[PDB]
Image (spheres, coloured by chain):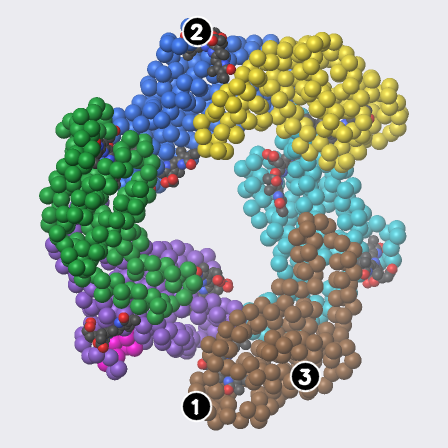
Chain colours: A purple, B cyan, C blue, D brown, E yellow, F green
Amino acid sequence: MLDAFAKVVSQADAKGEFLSNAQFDALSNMVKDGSKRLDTVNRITSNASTIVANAARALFEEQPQLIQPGGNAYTNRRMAACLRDMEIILRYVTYATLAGDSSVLDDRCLNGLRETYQALGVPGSSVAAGVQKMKEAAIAIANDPNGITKGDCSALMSEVASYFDRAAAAVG
Amino acid sequence: MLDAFAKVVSQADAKGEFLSNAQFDALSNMVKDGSKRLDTVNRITSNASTIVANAARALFEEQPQLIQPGGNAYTNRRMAACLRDMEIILRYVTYATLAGDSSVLDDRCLNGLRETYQALGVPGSSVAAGVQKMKEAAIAIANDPNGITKGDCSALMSEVASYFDRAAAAVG
Amino acid sequence: MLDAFAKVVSQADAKGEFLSNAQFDALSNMVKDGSKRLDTVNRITSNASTIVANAARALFEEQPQLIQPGGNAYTNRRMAACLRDMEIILRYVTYATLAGDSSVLDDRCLNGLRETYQALGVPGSSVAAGVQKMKEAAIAIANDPNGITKGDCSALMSEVASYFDRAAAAVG
Amino acid sequence: MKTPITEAIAAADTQGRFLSNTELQAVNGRFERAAASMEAARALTNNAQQLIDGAANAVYQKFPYTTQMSGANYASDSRGKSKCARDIGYYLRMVTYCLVAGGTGPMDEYLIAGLDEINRTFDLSPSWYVEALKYIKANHGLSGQAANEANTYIDYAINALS
Amino acid sequence: MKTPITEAIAAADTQGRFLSNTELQAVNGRFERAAASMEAARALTNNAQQLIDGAANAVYQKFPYTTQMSGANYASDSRGKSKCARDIGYYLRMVTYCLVAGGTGPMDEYLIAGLDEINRTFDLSPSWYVEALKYIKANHGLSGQAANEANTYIDYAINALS
Amino acid sequence: MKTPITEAIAAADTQGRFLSNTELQAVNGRFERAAASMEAARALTNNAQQLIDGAANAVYQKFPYTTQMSGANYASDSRGKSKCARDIGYYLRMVTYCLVAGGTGPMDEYLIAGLDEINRTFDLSPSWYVEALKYIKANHGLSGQAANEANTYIDYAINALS
Ligand SMILES: *[C@H](C)[C@H]1/C(=C/c2[nH]c(/C=C3N=C(/C=C4\NC(=O)C(CC)=C4C)C(C)=C\3CCC(=O)O)c(CCC(=O)O)c2C)NC(=O)[C@@H]1C
Ligand SMILES: *[C@H](C)[C@H]1/C(=C/c2[nH]c(/C=C3N=C(/C=C4\NC(=O)C(CC)=C4C)C(C)=C\3CCC(=O)O)c(CCC(=O)O)c2C)NC(=O)[C@@H]1C
Ligand SMILES: *[C@H](C)[C@H]1/C(=C/c2[nH]c(/C=C3N=C(/C=C4\NC(=O)C(CC)=C4C)C(C)=C\3CCC(=O)O)c(CCC(=O)O)c2C)NC(=O)[C@@H]1C
Ligand SMILES: *[C@H](C)[C@H]1/C(=C/c2[nH]c(/C=C3N=C(/C=C4\NC(=O)C(CC)=C4C)C(C)=C\3CCC(=O)O)c(CCC(=O)O)c2C)NC(=O)[C@@H]1C
Ligand SMILES: *[C@H](C)[C@H]1/C(=C/c2[nH]c(/C=C3N=C(/C=C4\NC(=O)C(CC)=C4C)C(C)=C\3CCC(=O)O)c(CCC(=O)O)c2C)NC(=O)[C@@H]1C
Ligand SMILES: *[C@H](C)[C@H]1/C(=C/c2[nH]c(/C=C3N=C(/C=C4\NC(=O)C(CC)=C4C)C(C)=C\3CCC(=O)O)c(CCC(=O)O)c2C)NC(=O)[C@@H]1C
Ligand SMILES: *[C@H](C)[C@H]1/C(=C/c2[nH]c(/C=C3N=C(/C=C4\NC(=O)C(CC)=C4C)C(C)=C\3CCC(=O)O)c(CCC(=O)O)c2C)NC(=O)[C@@H]1C
Ligand SMILES: *[C@H](C)[C@H]1/C(=C/c2[nH]c(/C=C3N=C(/C=C4\NC(=O)C(CC)=C4C)C(C)=C\3CCC(=O)O)c(CCC(=O)O)c2C)NC(=O)[C@@H]1C
Ligand SMILES: *[C@H](C)[C@H]1/C(=C/c2[nH]c(/C=C3N=C(/C=C4\NC(=O)C(CC)=C4C)C(C)=C\3CCC(=O)O)c(CCC(=O)O)c2C)NC(=O)[C@@H]1C
C-alpha cells in the first residue's frame, strides 16, 4: 500500500528521477494539515461504534426487507456480519485518511468485494446506502467546530468523502 | 448438510413461520419408518465389501477395456482408486438414506465429480454402470424378507434407488 | 518425471508389452554416450555462474531498456529475479540433459511460465534472447576439445540445443 | 445444522467410514425421543401468541424501566414493544425448531451465533430474555417428557444468555 | 518414476541446486550396470512365455487347491487360469521394466502401490505370487551378474509380497 | 512500501482494528521530524551532481586499482566510470527517497533487496560503495537534525554493505 509520500517516490523511481521542486512542495503541503488529519481519524475512530450502529439502524428502517425473516441481515450471525462489514469499511476509510491515499482501501477492502457480495447474495445496493449514512455521520463528527482549535478542514472533509463515495461505488 | 427434519425447519425459518399441521404430520411420518431406514443402512453397510467387489467384477466383465493394459482401471493404484470410488459413492448413498435427504450426497461427493472425471480421463459412463450394479445389489440385500419383521419398504427402496440414480446421473 | 529409459518403459506398459528388439537397442545405444553425457553436465554445471553472468551482461548490452530506471531488470530485486530465472532455466536444461528427456524441463520449469511472465510484465522475448546466449556459451564449453579423451559429441550437442530452444520457445 | 442424524453422518464422514452401529443406535435414540419432542413443539406452536404476549408482559413487570426509559434499546414506545414481542417470538420459534430437529442446531445457527455481539451492539440486556424464557417454561402447561424436552432447550437458551 | 537418474535430479531439484559430483558419480554407477541389466531383460523377455507357463504350473503344483476349489479368486476353470497367467506375466514384465530403468520405480508404480488392497479385495493369496516369483528366479538360468541384477528385483517382489 | 504511516496502518490491520493513539502519536512523530527530513532531501537533490562526482573520485582515490585493472566490473574505461557514477547516483537518490518517505522503505525495496547477490554476480566490492557513502556524509553540508536524518540513512546503507 502507498501513502502520499510513497506514491511520489514510486513514480519518481520509475523515471529515474530525484524529486522535483513542485513535488517537494506538494508533499510539504500534506505535513501542514497533518494535525488536522489526525483529529479526523481520532474523532471518526473514537465514535466508530456510534457511526456503525446508527447507520445500520437507519439502514434497516429504510430497507425493512433486510431484517425480515429471510432477509440478508436476518439471524444474528448475518446481522453481526453486516455490522462487521460496516466497521471494516469505516476502518479502511480511516486508514486511507491517515495515508492520504486510497491504495490501502482499494487493495485490502474493495478489489474483489463486488464479486464476493454477488456470490453470496449480499444486497450490494444496500451496503452502498449503508456507507452513505456512515459518511455523513463521520464527516459531521470530524468537522464539528466544538472542542478544537477552530480552523478550516474542508480539504480533508472532501478527501474523506471521496473515500466513502469510493467504497459505495465499489459495491453499489 | 440437511436431514429431512432440518430441511423443513430451514424453509420454515426463511419464511419466519412456526411449523404447520401439514409439516408436523410429514416429519412424524419419517419417524414411522425410522426403524426400517436403520435396517436399510445396516444391511447395505454390513455388505459394502460384497456389493463393491461384485459390482466391480461385473463391470470389468462387461467392459474389459478397463482391465487391459493402458485401461483406466489397470495397475493396482488405479484399481484401488476405482474400488475406492465405488465404496465412497455407496457410503454417500447410505448417509443420504439415513438422513432422508440427498443434500449430503450432492454436496460432499457428487458436486464437480464429473468435471474431475473428465479432467482425469475416468470414463464417467463406466462409473455410472458400476453405480447401477451396486443399486440392484444393495436394494436386493436391503429388501430381502429373511431375518426381519415382514412389512413394506417399497417407499424407502424407491428413495434408495433415487440416491443411486442421482450418482449415476452426476458422472455418466 | 521421466528419463529416456523410464519413458520407453512407460509407453510399453500402456501397451501391455515387453520391450521390442528396437527399444532394447535404442536404450543400450543411449548408454554408449553415457560417459560423454556426464562430461556435458559436469562442464556446463561447473561453469554455470559464468554462463549466466556473461549471458545477462550480453543481454543487457543488446537491450539497454531492461536496466534503465523503470525497465524490468532495474532495482536489485528485479535484477536478482532475472538472474535467478536464467540460472533456473540453465539448471533444468542440465537436468533434462542428464535424463535424455525434456519432461522435467517442461513439467517443473516451462509448463505455465509464459502466462506468468505475461502476468508480471516480463519481456518474454528478452528472456529468450538470454536463453539463446546461454545456449551458445553452454555448448561451446561442452564441446570444447581440451582436457578429455577426444571423440564425437555432436549428437549430445544437438540434444542440448533442443532443450535450450525448447525453453526459448516456451516464453519468447 | 447440527441434528443428531447430521452429526452421526459428520462423524462417520470425518473418519471416512460407513455408519457405525454406535451411530445407528444414537439415531434410534432420537427416534424414541421424537414423540416427546413433537408433543411439546405442537403445543408451543398452538399457544405461540399467548406465550409471547405472556412473556413480554412478565418482562415489562420484572424490569419496569424498559417501558419508562428513553432509548432505541427500550420498550417505552410502540416501536420497541413490537421489536421486543418479535424478539420473544424468535426465541420461541427457535425452541419449536430444536424440538423438531431433536437438537440445538437451529437455535445455535439462527440465533446464538452472533448473539453476544448483537446484544452488546444494540445494548439489549440478556436478562430480559432470560425472564421471557422462564415465563415460557413456567407456563407451557406440559408434563412428562414433553415438558423435559422443552425445558432442556429453553434452559439452553438461558445458559446461552448467562 | 524412480530411476536413479530422476532420483538424482529430484534430490538436486529439492535443494534448488545443480547436480553434484556425488550425483554424477551415482549415475555412472547406473550407466555401467546398464550392461548386465539390459541383457537380463532381453533373456527374460525372449523366454517370457515359457517362464510364465512354467511359473503358473509351479504355483498350481505347490497349491493344488487353487486349481480345484471354485470361486472367482481361484484357477479352477479357464478364466481363472487365464487371470493367473496374466498376473504372473505382469510380474515378469515389471522385472523387465525395472532392469531397463535401473531400479524399482516401474514395479513400485505399476504394481506395488495398491497391491495389498487388491489381494485383500479379490482374496488372492500373496503366497501364490511368491511361488511364481521363485520359479522365475530358479529358471531364468542367468549366472553371475546378469543374474545378480534380475534376482534383486525378483527378491524385491517377494519382499513386497511379505 | 515501508513508511511510518503504512507501518501504523499495517499494524492496525493485522489486529483487524482501528488505528490507536499509539499509532496516531507515531505518525505525529513523522510529521514533527518531516521538517528536518525534507530539508536534507532538498539540498542533496540540489548538490546531486557535485556529490556524485565527488563520491566517485573519493572511491578512485581509496581504490586506485579500480581505474587500472582490466575487467567489465572495474572503472578503467569510460563505460565502467559511467556505471559507477550511475550507481552512486542511485544510492544518493535512495537516500533522498528515504528522507521524503520518513524511513528506509524505498532504499529497502529498490536497492537493498537483492544487493548481496548483485554485488557477487557482478564482482562489485561493497567497500567501494561504502567509501562513496562516506564522502556523501562528509560533504552534504547539512547540520542540526537534517544532518542527522541524512546520516541515519547513509549509515543505514553503509551497514547494509558491511
Ligand atoms: C450490512 C450493511 C450488509 C450485509 C453484510 C454481510 N456480509 C456477509 C459476508 C461477508 N462479508 C465479507 C466481506 C469482507 N470480509 C473481509 O474480511 C473484508 C475485507 C477486510 C470484507 C470487506 C466476506 C468475505 C463475507 C463472507 C464471510 C463471512 O461471512 O464472514 C454476510 C453474511 C452472509 C452469509 O451467508 O453468512 C452479510 C449479512 N448484509 C446485508 O444484507 C447488509 C446490506
Ligand atoms: C478539522 C476537521 C477541525 C480542526 C482541526 C485542527 N486541529 C488543530 C491543531 C491540533 N490538532 C492536534 C491533534 C493531534 N495531534 C496529535 O499528535 C494527535 C494524536 C496523538 C492528534 C489527534 C494537535 C496536537 C494540534 C496542535 C495544538 C492545538 O491545540 O491546536 C488545528 C490548528 C492548525 C494546525 O494544523 O496546527 C486545527 C484547525 N479545527 C476545526 O475547527 C476543524 C473543524
Ligand atoms: C471405477 C469404477 C472407475 C475408475 C475410477 C477412478 N477414480 C480415480 C480417481 C479419483 N476419483 C475421485 C473421486 C472422489 N474422491 C473423493 O474424495 C470423492 C468424494 C469424497 C470422490 C467421489 C478423485 C478425487 C480422484 C482423483 C484423486 C485420487 O486418485 O485420489 C482413479 C485414479 C486416476 C489416476 O489417474 O490415478 C480411478 C482409476 N477407473 C475406472 O476405470 C473405472 C470406470
Ligand atoms: C425394510 C427394508 C424391510 C423390513 C424392515 C422392518 N424392520 C422393522 C422393525 C425393526 N427394525 C429394527 C432395527 C433397528 N433399530 C435400531 O435401533 C437399529 C440400530 C442398532 C436397527 C437396525 C427394530 C429395532 C425393529 C423393531 C423390532 C422388530 O424386530 O421388528 C419393521 C417393523 C415396523 C416398524 O416400524 O418397526 C419392518 C417392516 N421388513 C421387510 O419385510 C423389508 C424387507
Ligand atoms: C531476466 C533475463 C528477465 C527477467 C526476469 C524476472 N522474473 C521475475 C519473476 C519471476 N520469474 C519466475 C520464474 C520462475 N520461478 C520459479 O520457481 C520457476 C520454476 C522453478 C521459474 C522459471 C517467477 C515464478 C517469478 C515470480 C516470483 C518471483 O519474483 O520470485 C521477475 C520479477 C518480477 C517482479 O515484479 O518482481 C523478473 C524481473 N526480467 C527481465 O527484464 C529479464 C529479461
Ligand atoms: C564430448 C562433449 C567430449 C568428449 C567426451 C568423452 N569422454 C570420454 C570418456 C570419459 N569421460 C568420463 C566422464 C565421467 N564419468 C563419470 O563417472 C563422471 C562423473 C564423475 C564423468 C564426468 C569418463 C570417466 C571417461 C572415461 C575415461 C577417459 O578419461 O576417457 C570419451 C571417450 C569415449 C567414451 O564414450 O567413453 C569421450 C569422447 N570428448 C570429446 O572429444 C568431446 C569434445
Ligand atoms: C424485549 C425483551 C426487550 C427489547 C427488545 C428490542 N430488540 C431490538 C432489536 C434487536 N433485537 C434483535 C434480535 C434478533 N435478531 C435476529 O435476527 C435474532 C435471531 C433470529 C434475534 C434474537 C436484533 C438483531 C435487533 C437489532 C436489529 C433490528 O432492529 O431487528 C430493539 C430495538 C433496538 C434498536 O436499537 O433499534 C428492542 C427495543 N427492548 C426492551 O426494552 C424489551 C424489554
Ligand atoms: C495366479 C497366481 C493365481 C490367481 C490369480 C487371479 N487373479 C485375479 C484377478 C486379479 N489379478 C489382479 C492383478 C493385478 N492387476 C494389476 O493391474 C496388477 C499390476 C499391474 C496386478 C498384479 C487384479 C487387479 C485382479 C482383479 C481385477 C481383474 O480381474 O483384473 C483372478 C480373478 C479374481 C476375480 O474375483 O475375478 C484370479 C483367479 N488365482 C489363482 O487361483 C492362481 C493360483
Ligand atoms: C563504482 C563505485 C564502481 C564500479 C561500478 C560498476 N557497476 C556495474 C554494474 C552494476 N551496478 C549495479 C547496481 C545497481 N543496479 C540497480 O538497479 C541498483 C539499485 C537501484 C544498483 C545499486 C548493477 C545491478 C550492475 C550490473 C547490471 C548493470 O550493468 O546495470 C559495473 C559494470 C559491471 C559489468 O560486469 O558490466 C561497474 C563497472 N566499478 C568500479 O570499479 C567502481 C569503483
Residue D70: give its label. Answer: 1
- Residue C1 appears in the picture as rendered: yes
Chain for disc number 1: D
Q: Nearer the viewer, mark 3 or mark 2?
A: 2
Give the SS element for disc 2.
Answer: loop
Q: Residues within 10 Å of mark 3 (few under 14, many from 20)?
A: many
Front-lying residue, D56 or A93: A93
Q: Which residues are magenta?
A: A139-145
Q: Amino acid at mark 1?
A: Ser
Q: CA distance from mark 3 to mark 2?
A: 99 Å
Crowdedness near tag 2: few (<14), some (14–19) or many (≥20) residues, C-alpha within 10 Å: few
**Residue at numbered disc 3:** D137
Q: Residue furthest front?
A: F62
Task: Report the residue marked by disc 2.
Answer: C149
**Picture quarter containing residue C9?**
top right
In 3D space, how far apart are the residues under numbered discs 2 and 1 (Cα atoms)? 102 Å
Quadrant of the image containing the C terminus of chain F: top left
Please provide percent x and percent y for residue B91.
70, 48
Q: Is residue F11 left or right of residue C15?
A: left
- N-terminal of the pair, mark 1 or mark 3, is 1
Amino acid found under the numbered disc labelled 2 = Thr
Q: Position of residue A102 (x, y in %)?
A: 29, 59
- Residue at horizontal 68%, vertical 56%? D11
Given contact means CB atoms under 8 Å apart, are the residues at marks 2 and 1 in contact? no
Q: CA distance from mark 1 to mark 3?
A: 30 Å
Chain that bears disc 3: D
Q: Is residue D63 left or right of residue F45?
A: right
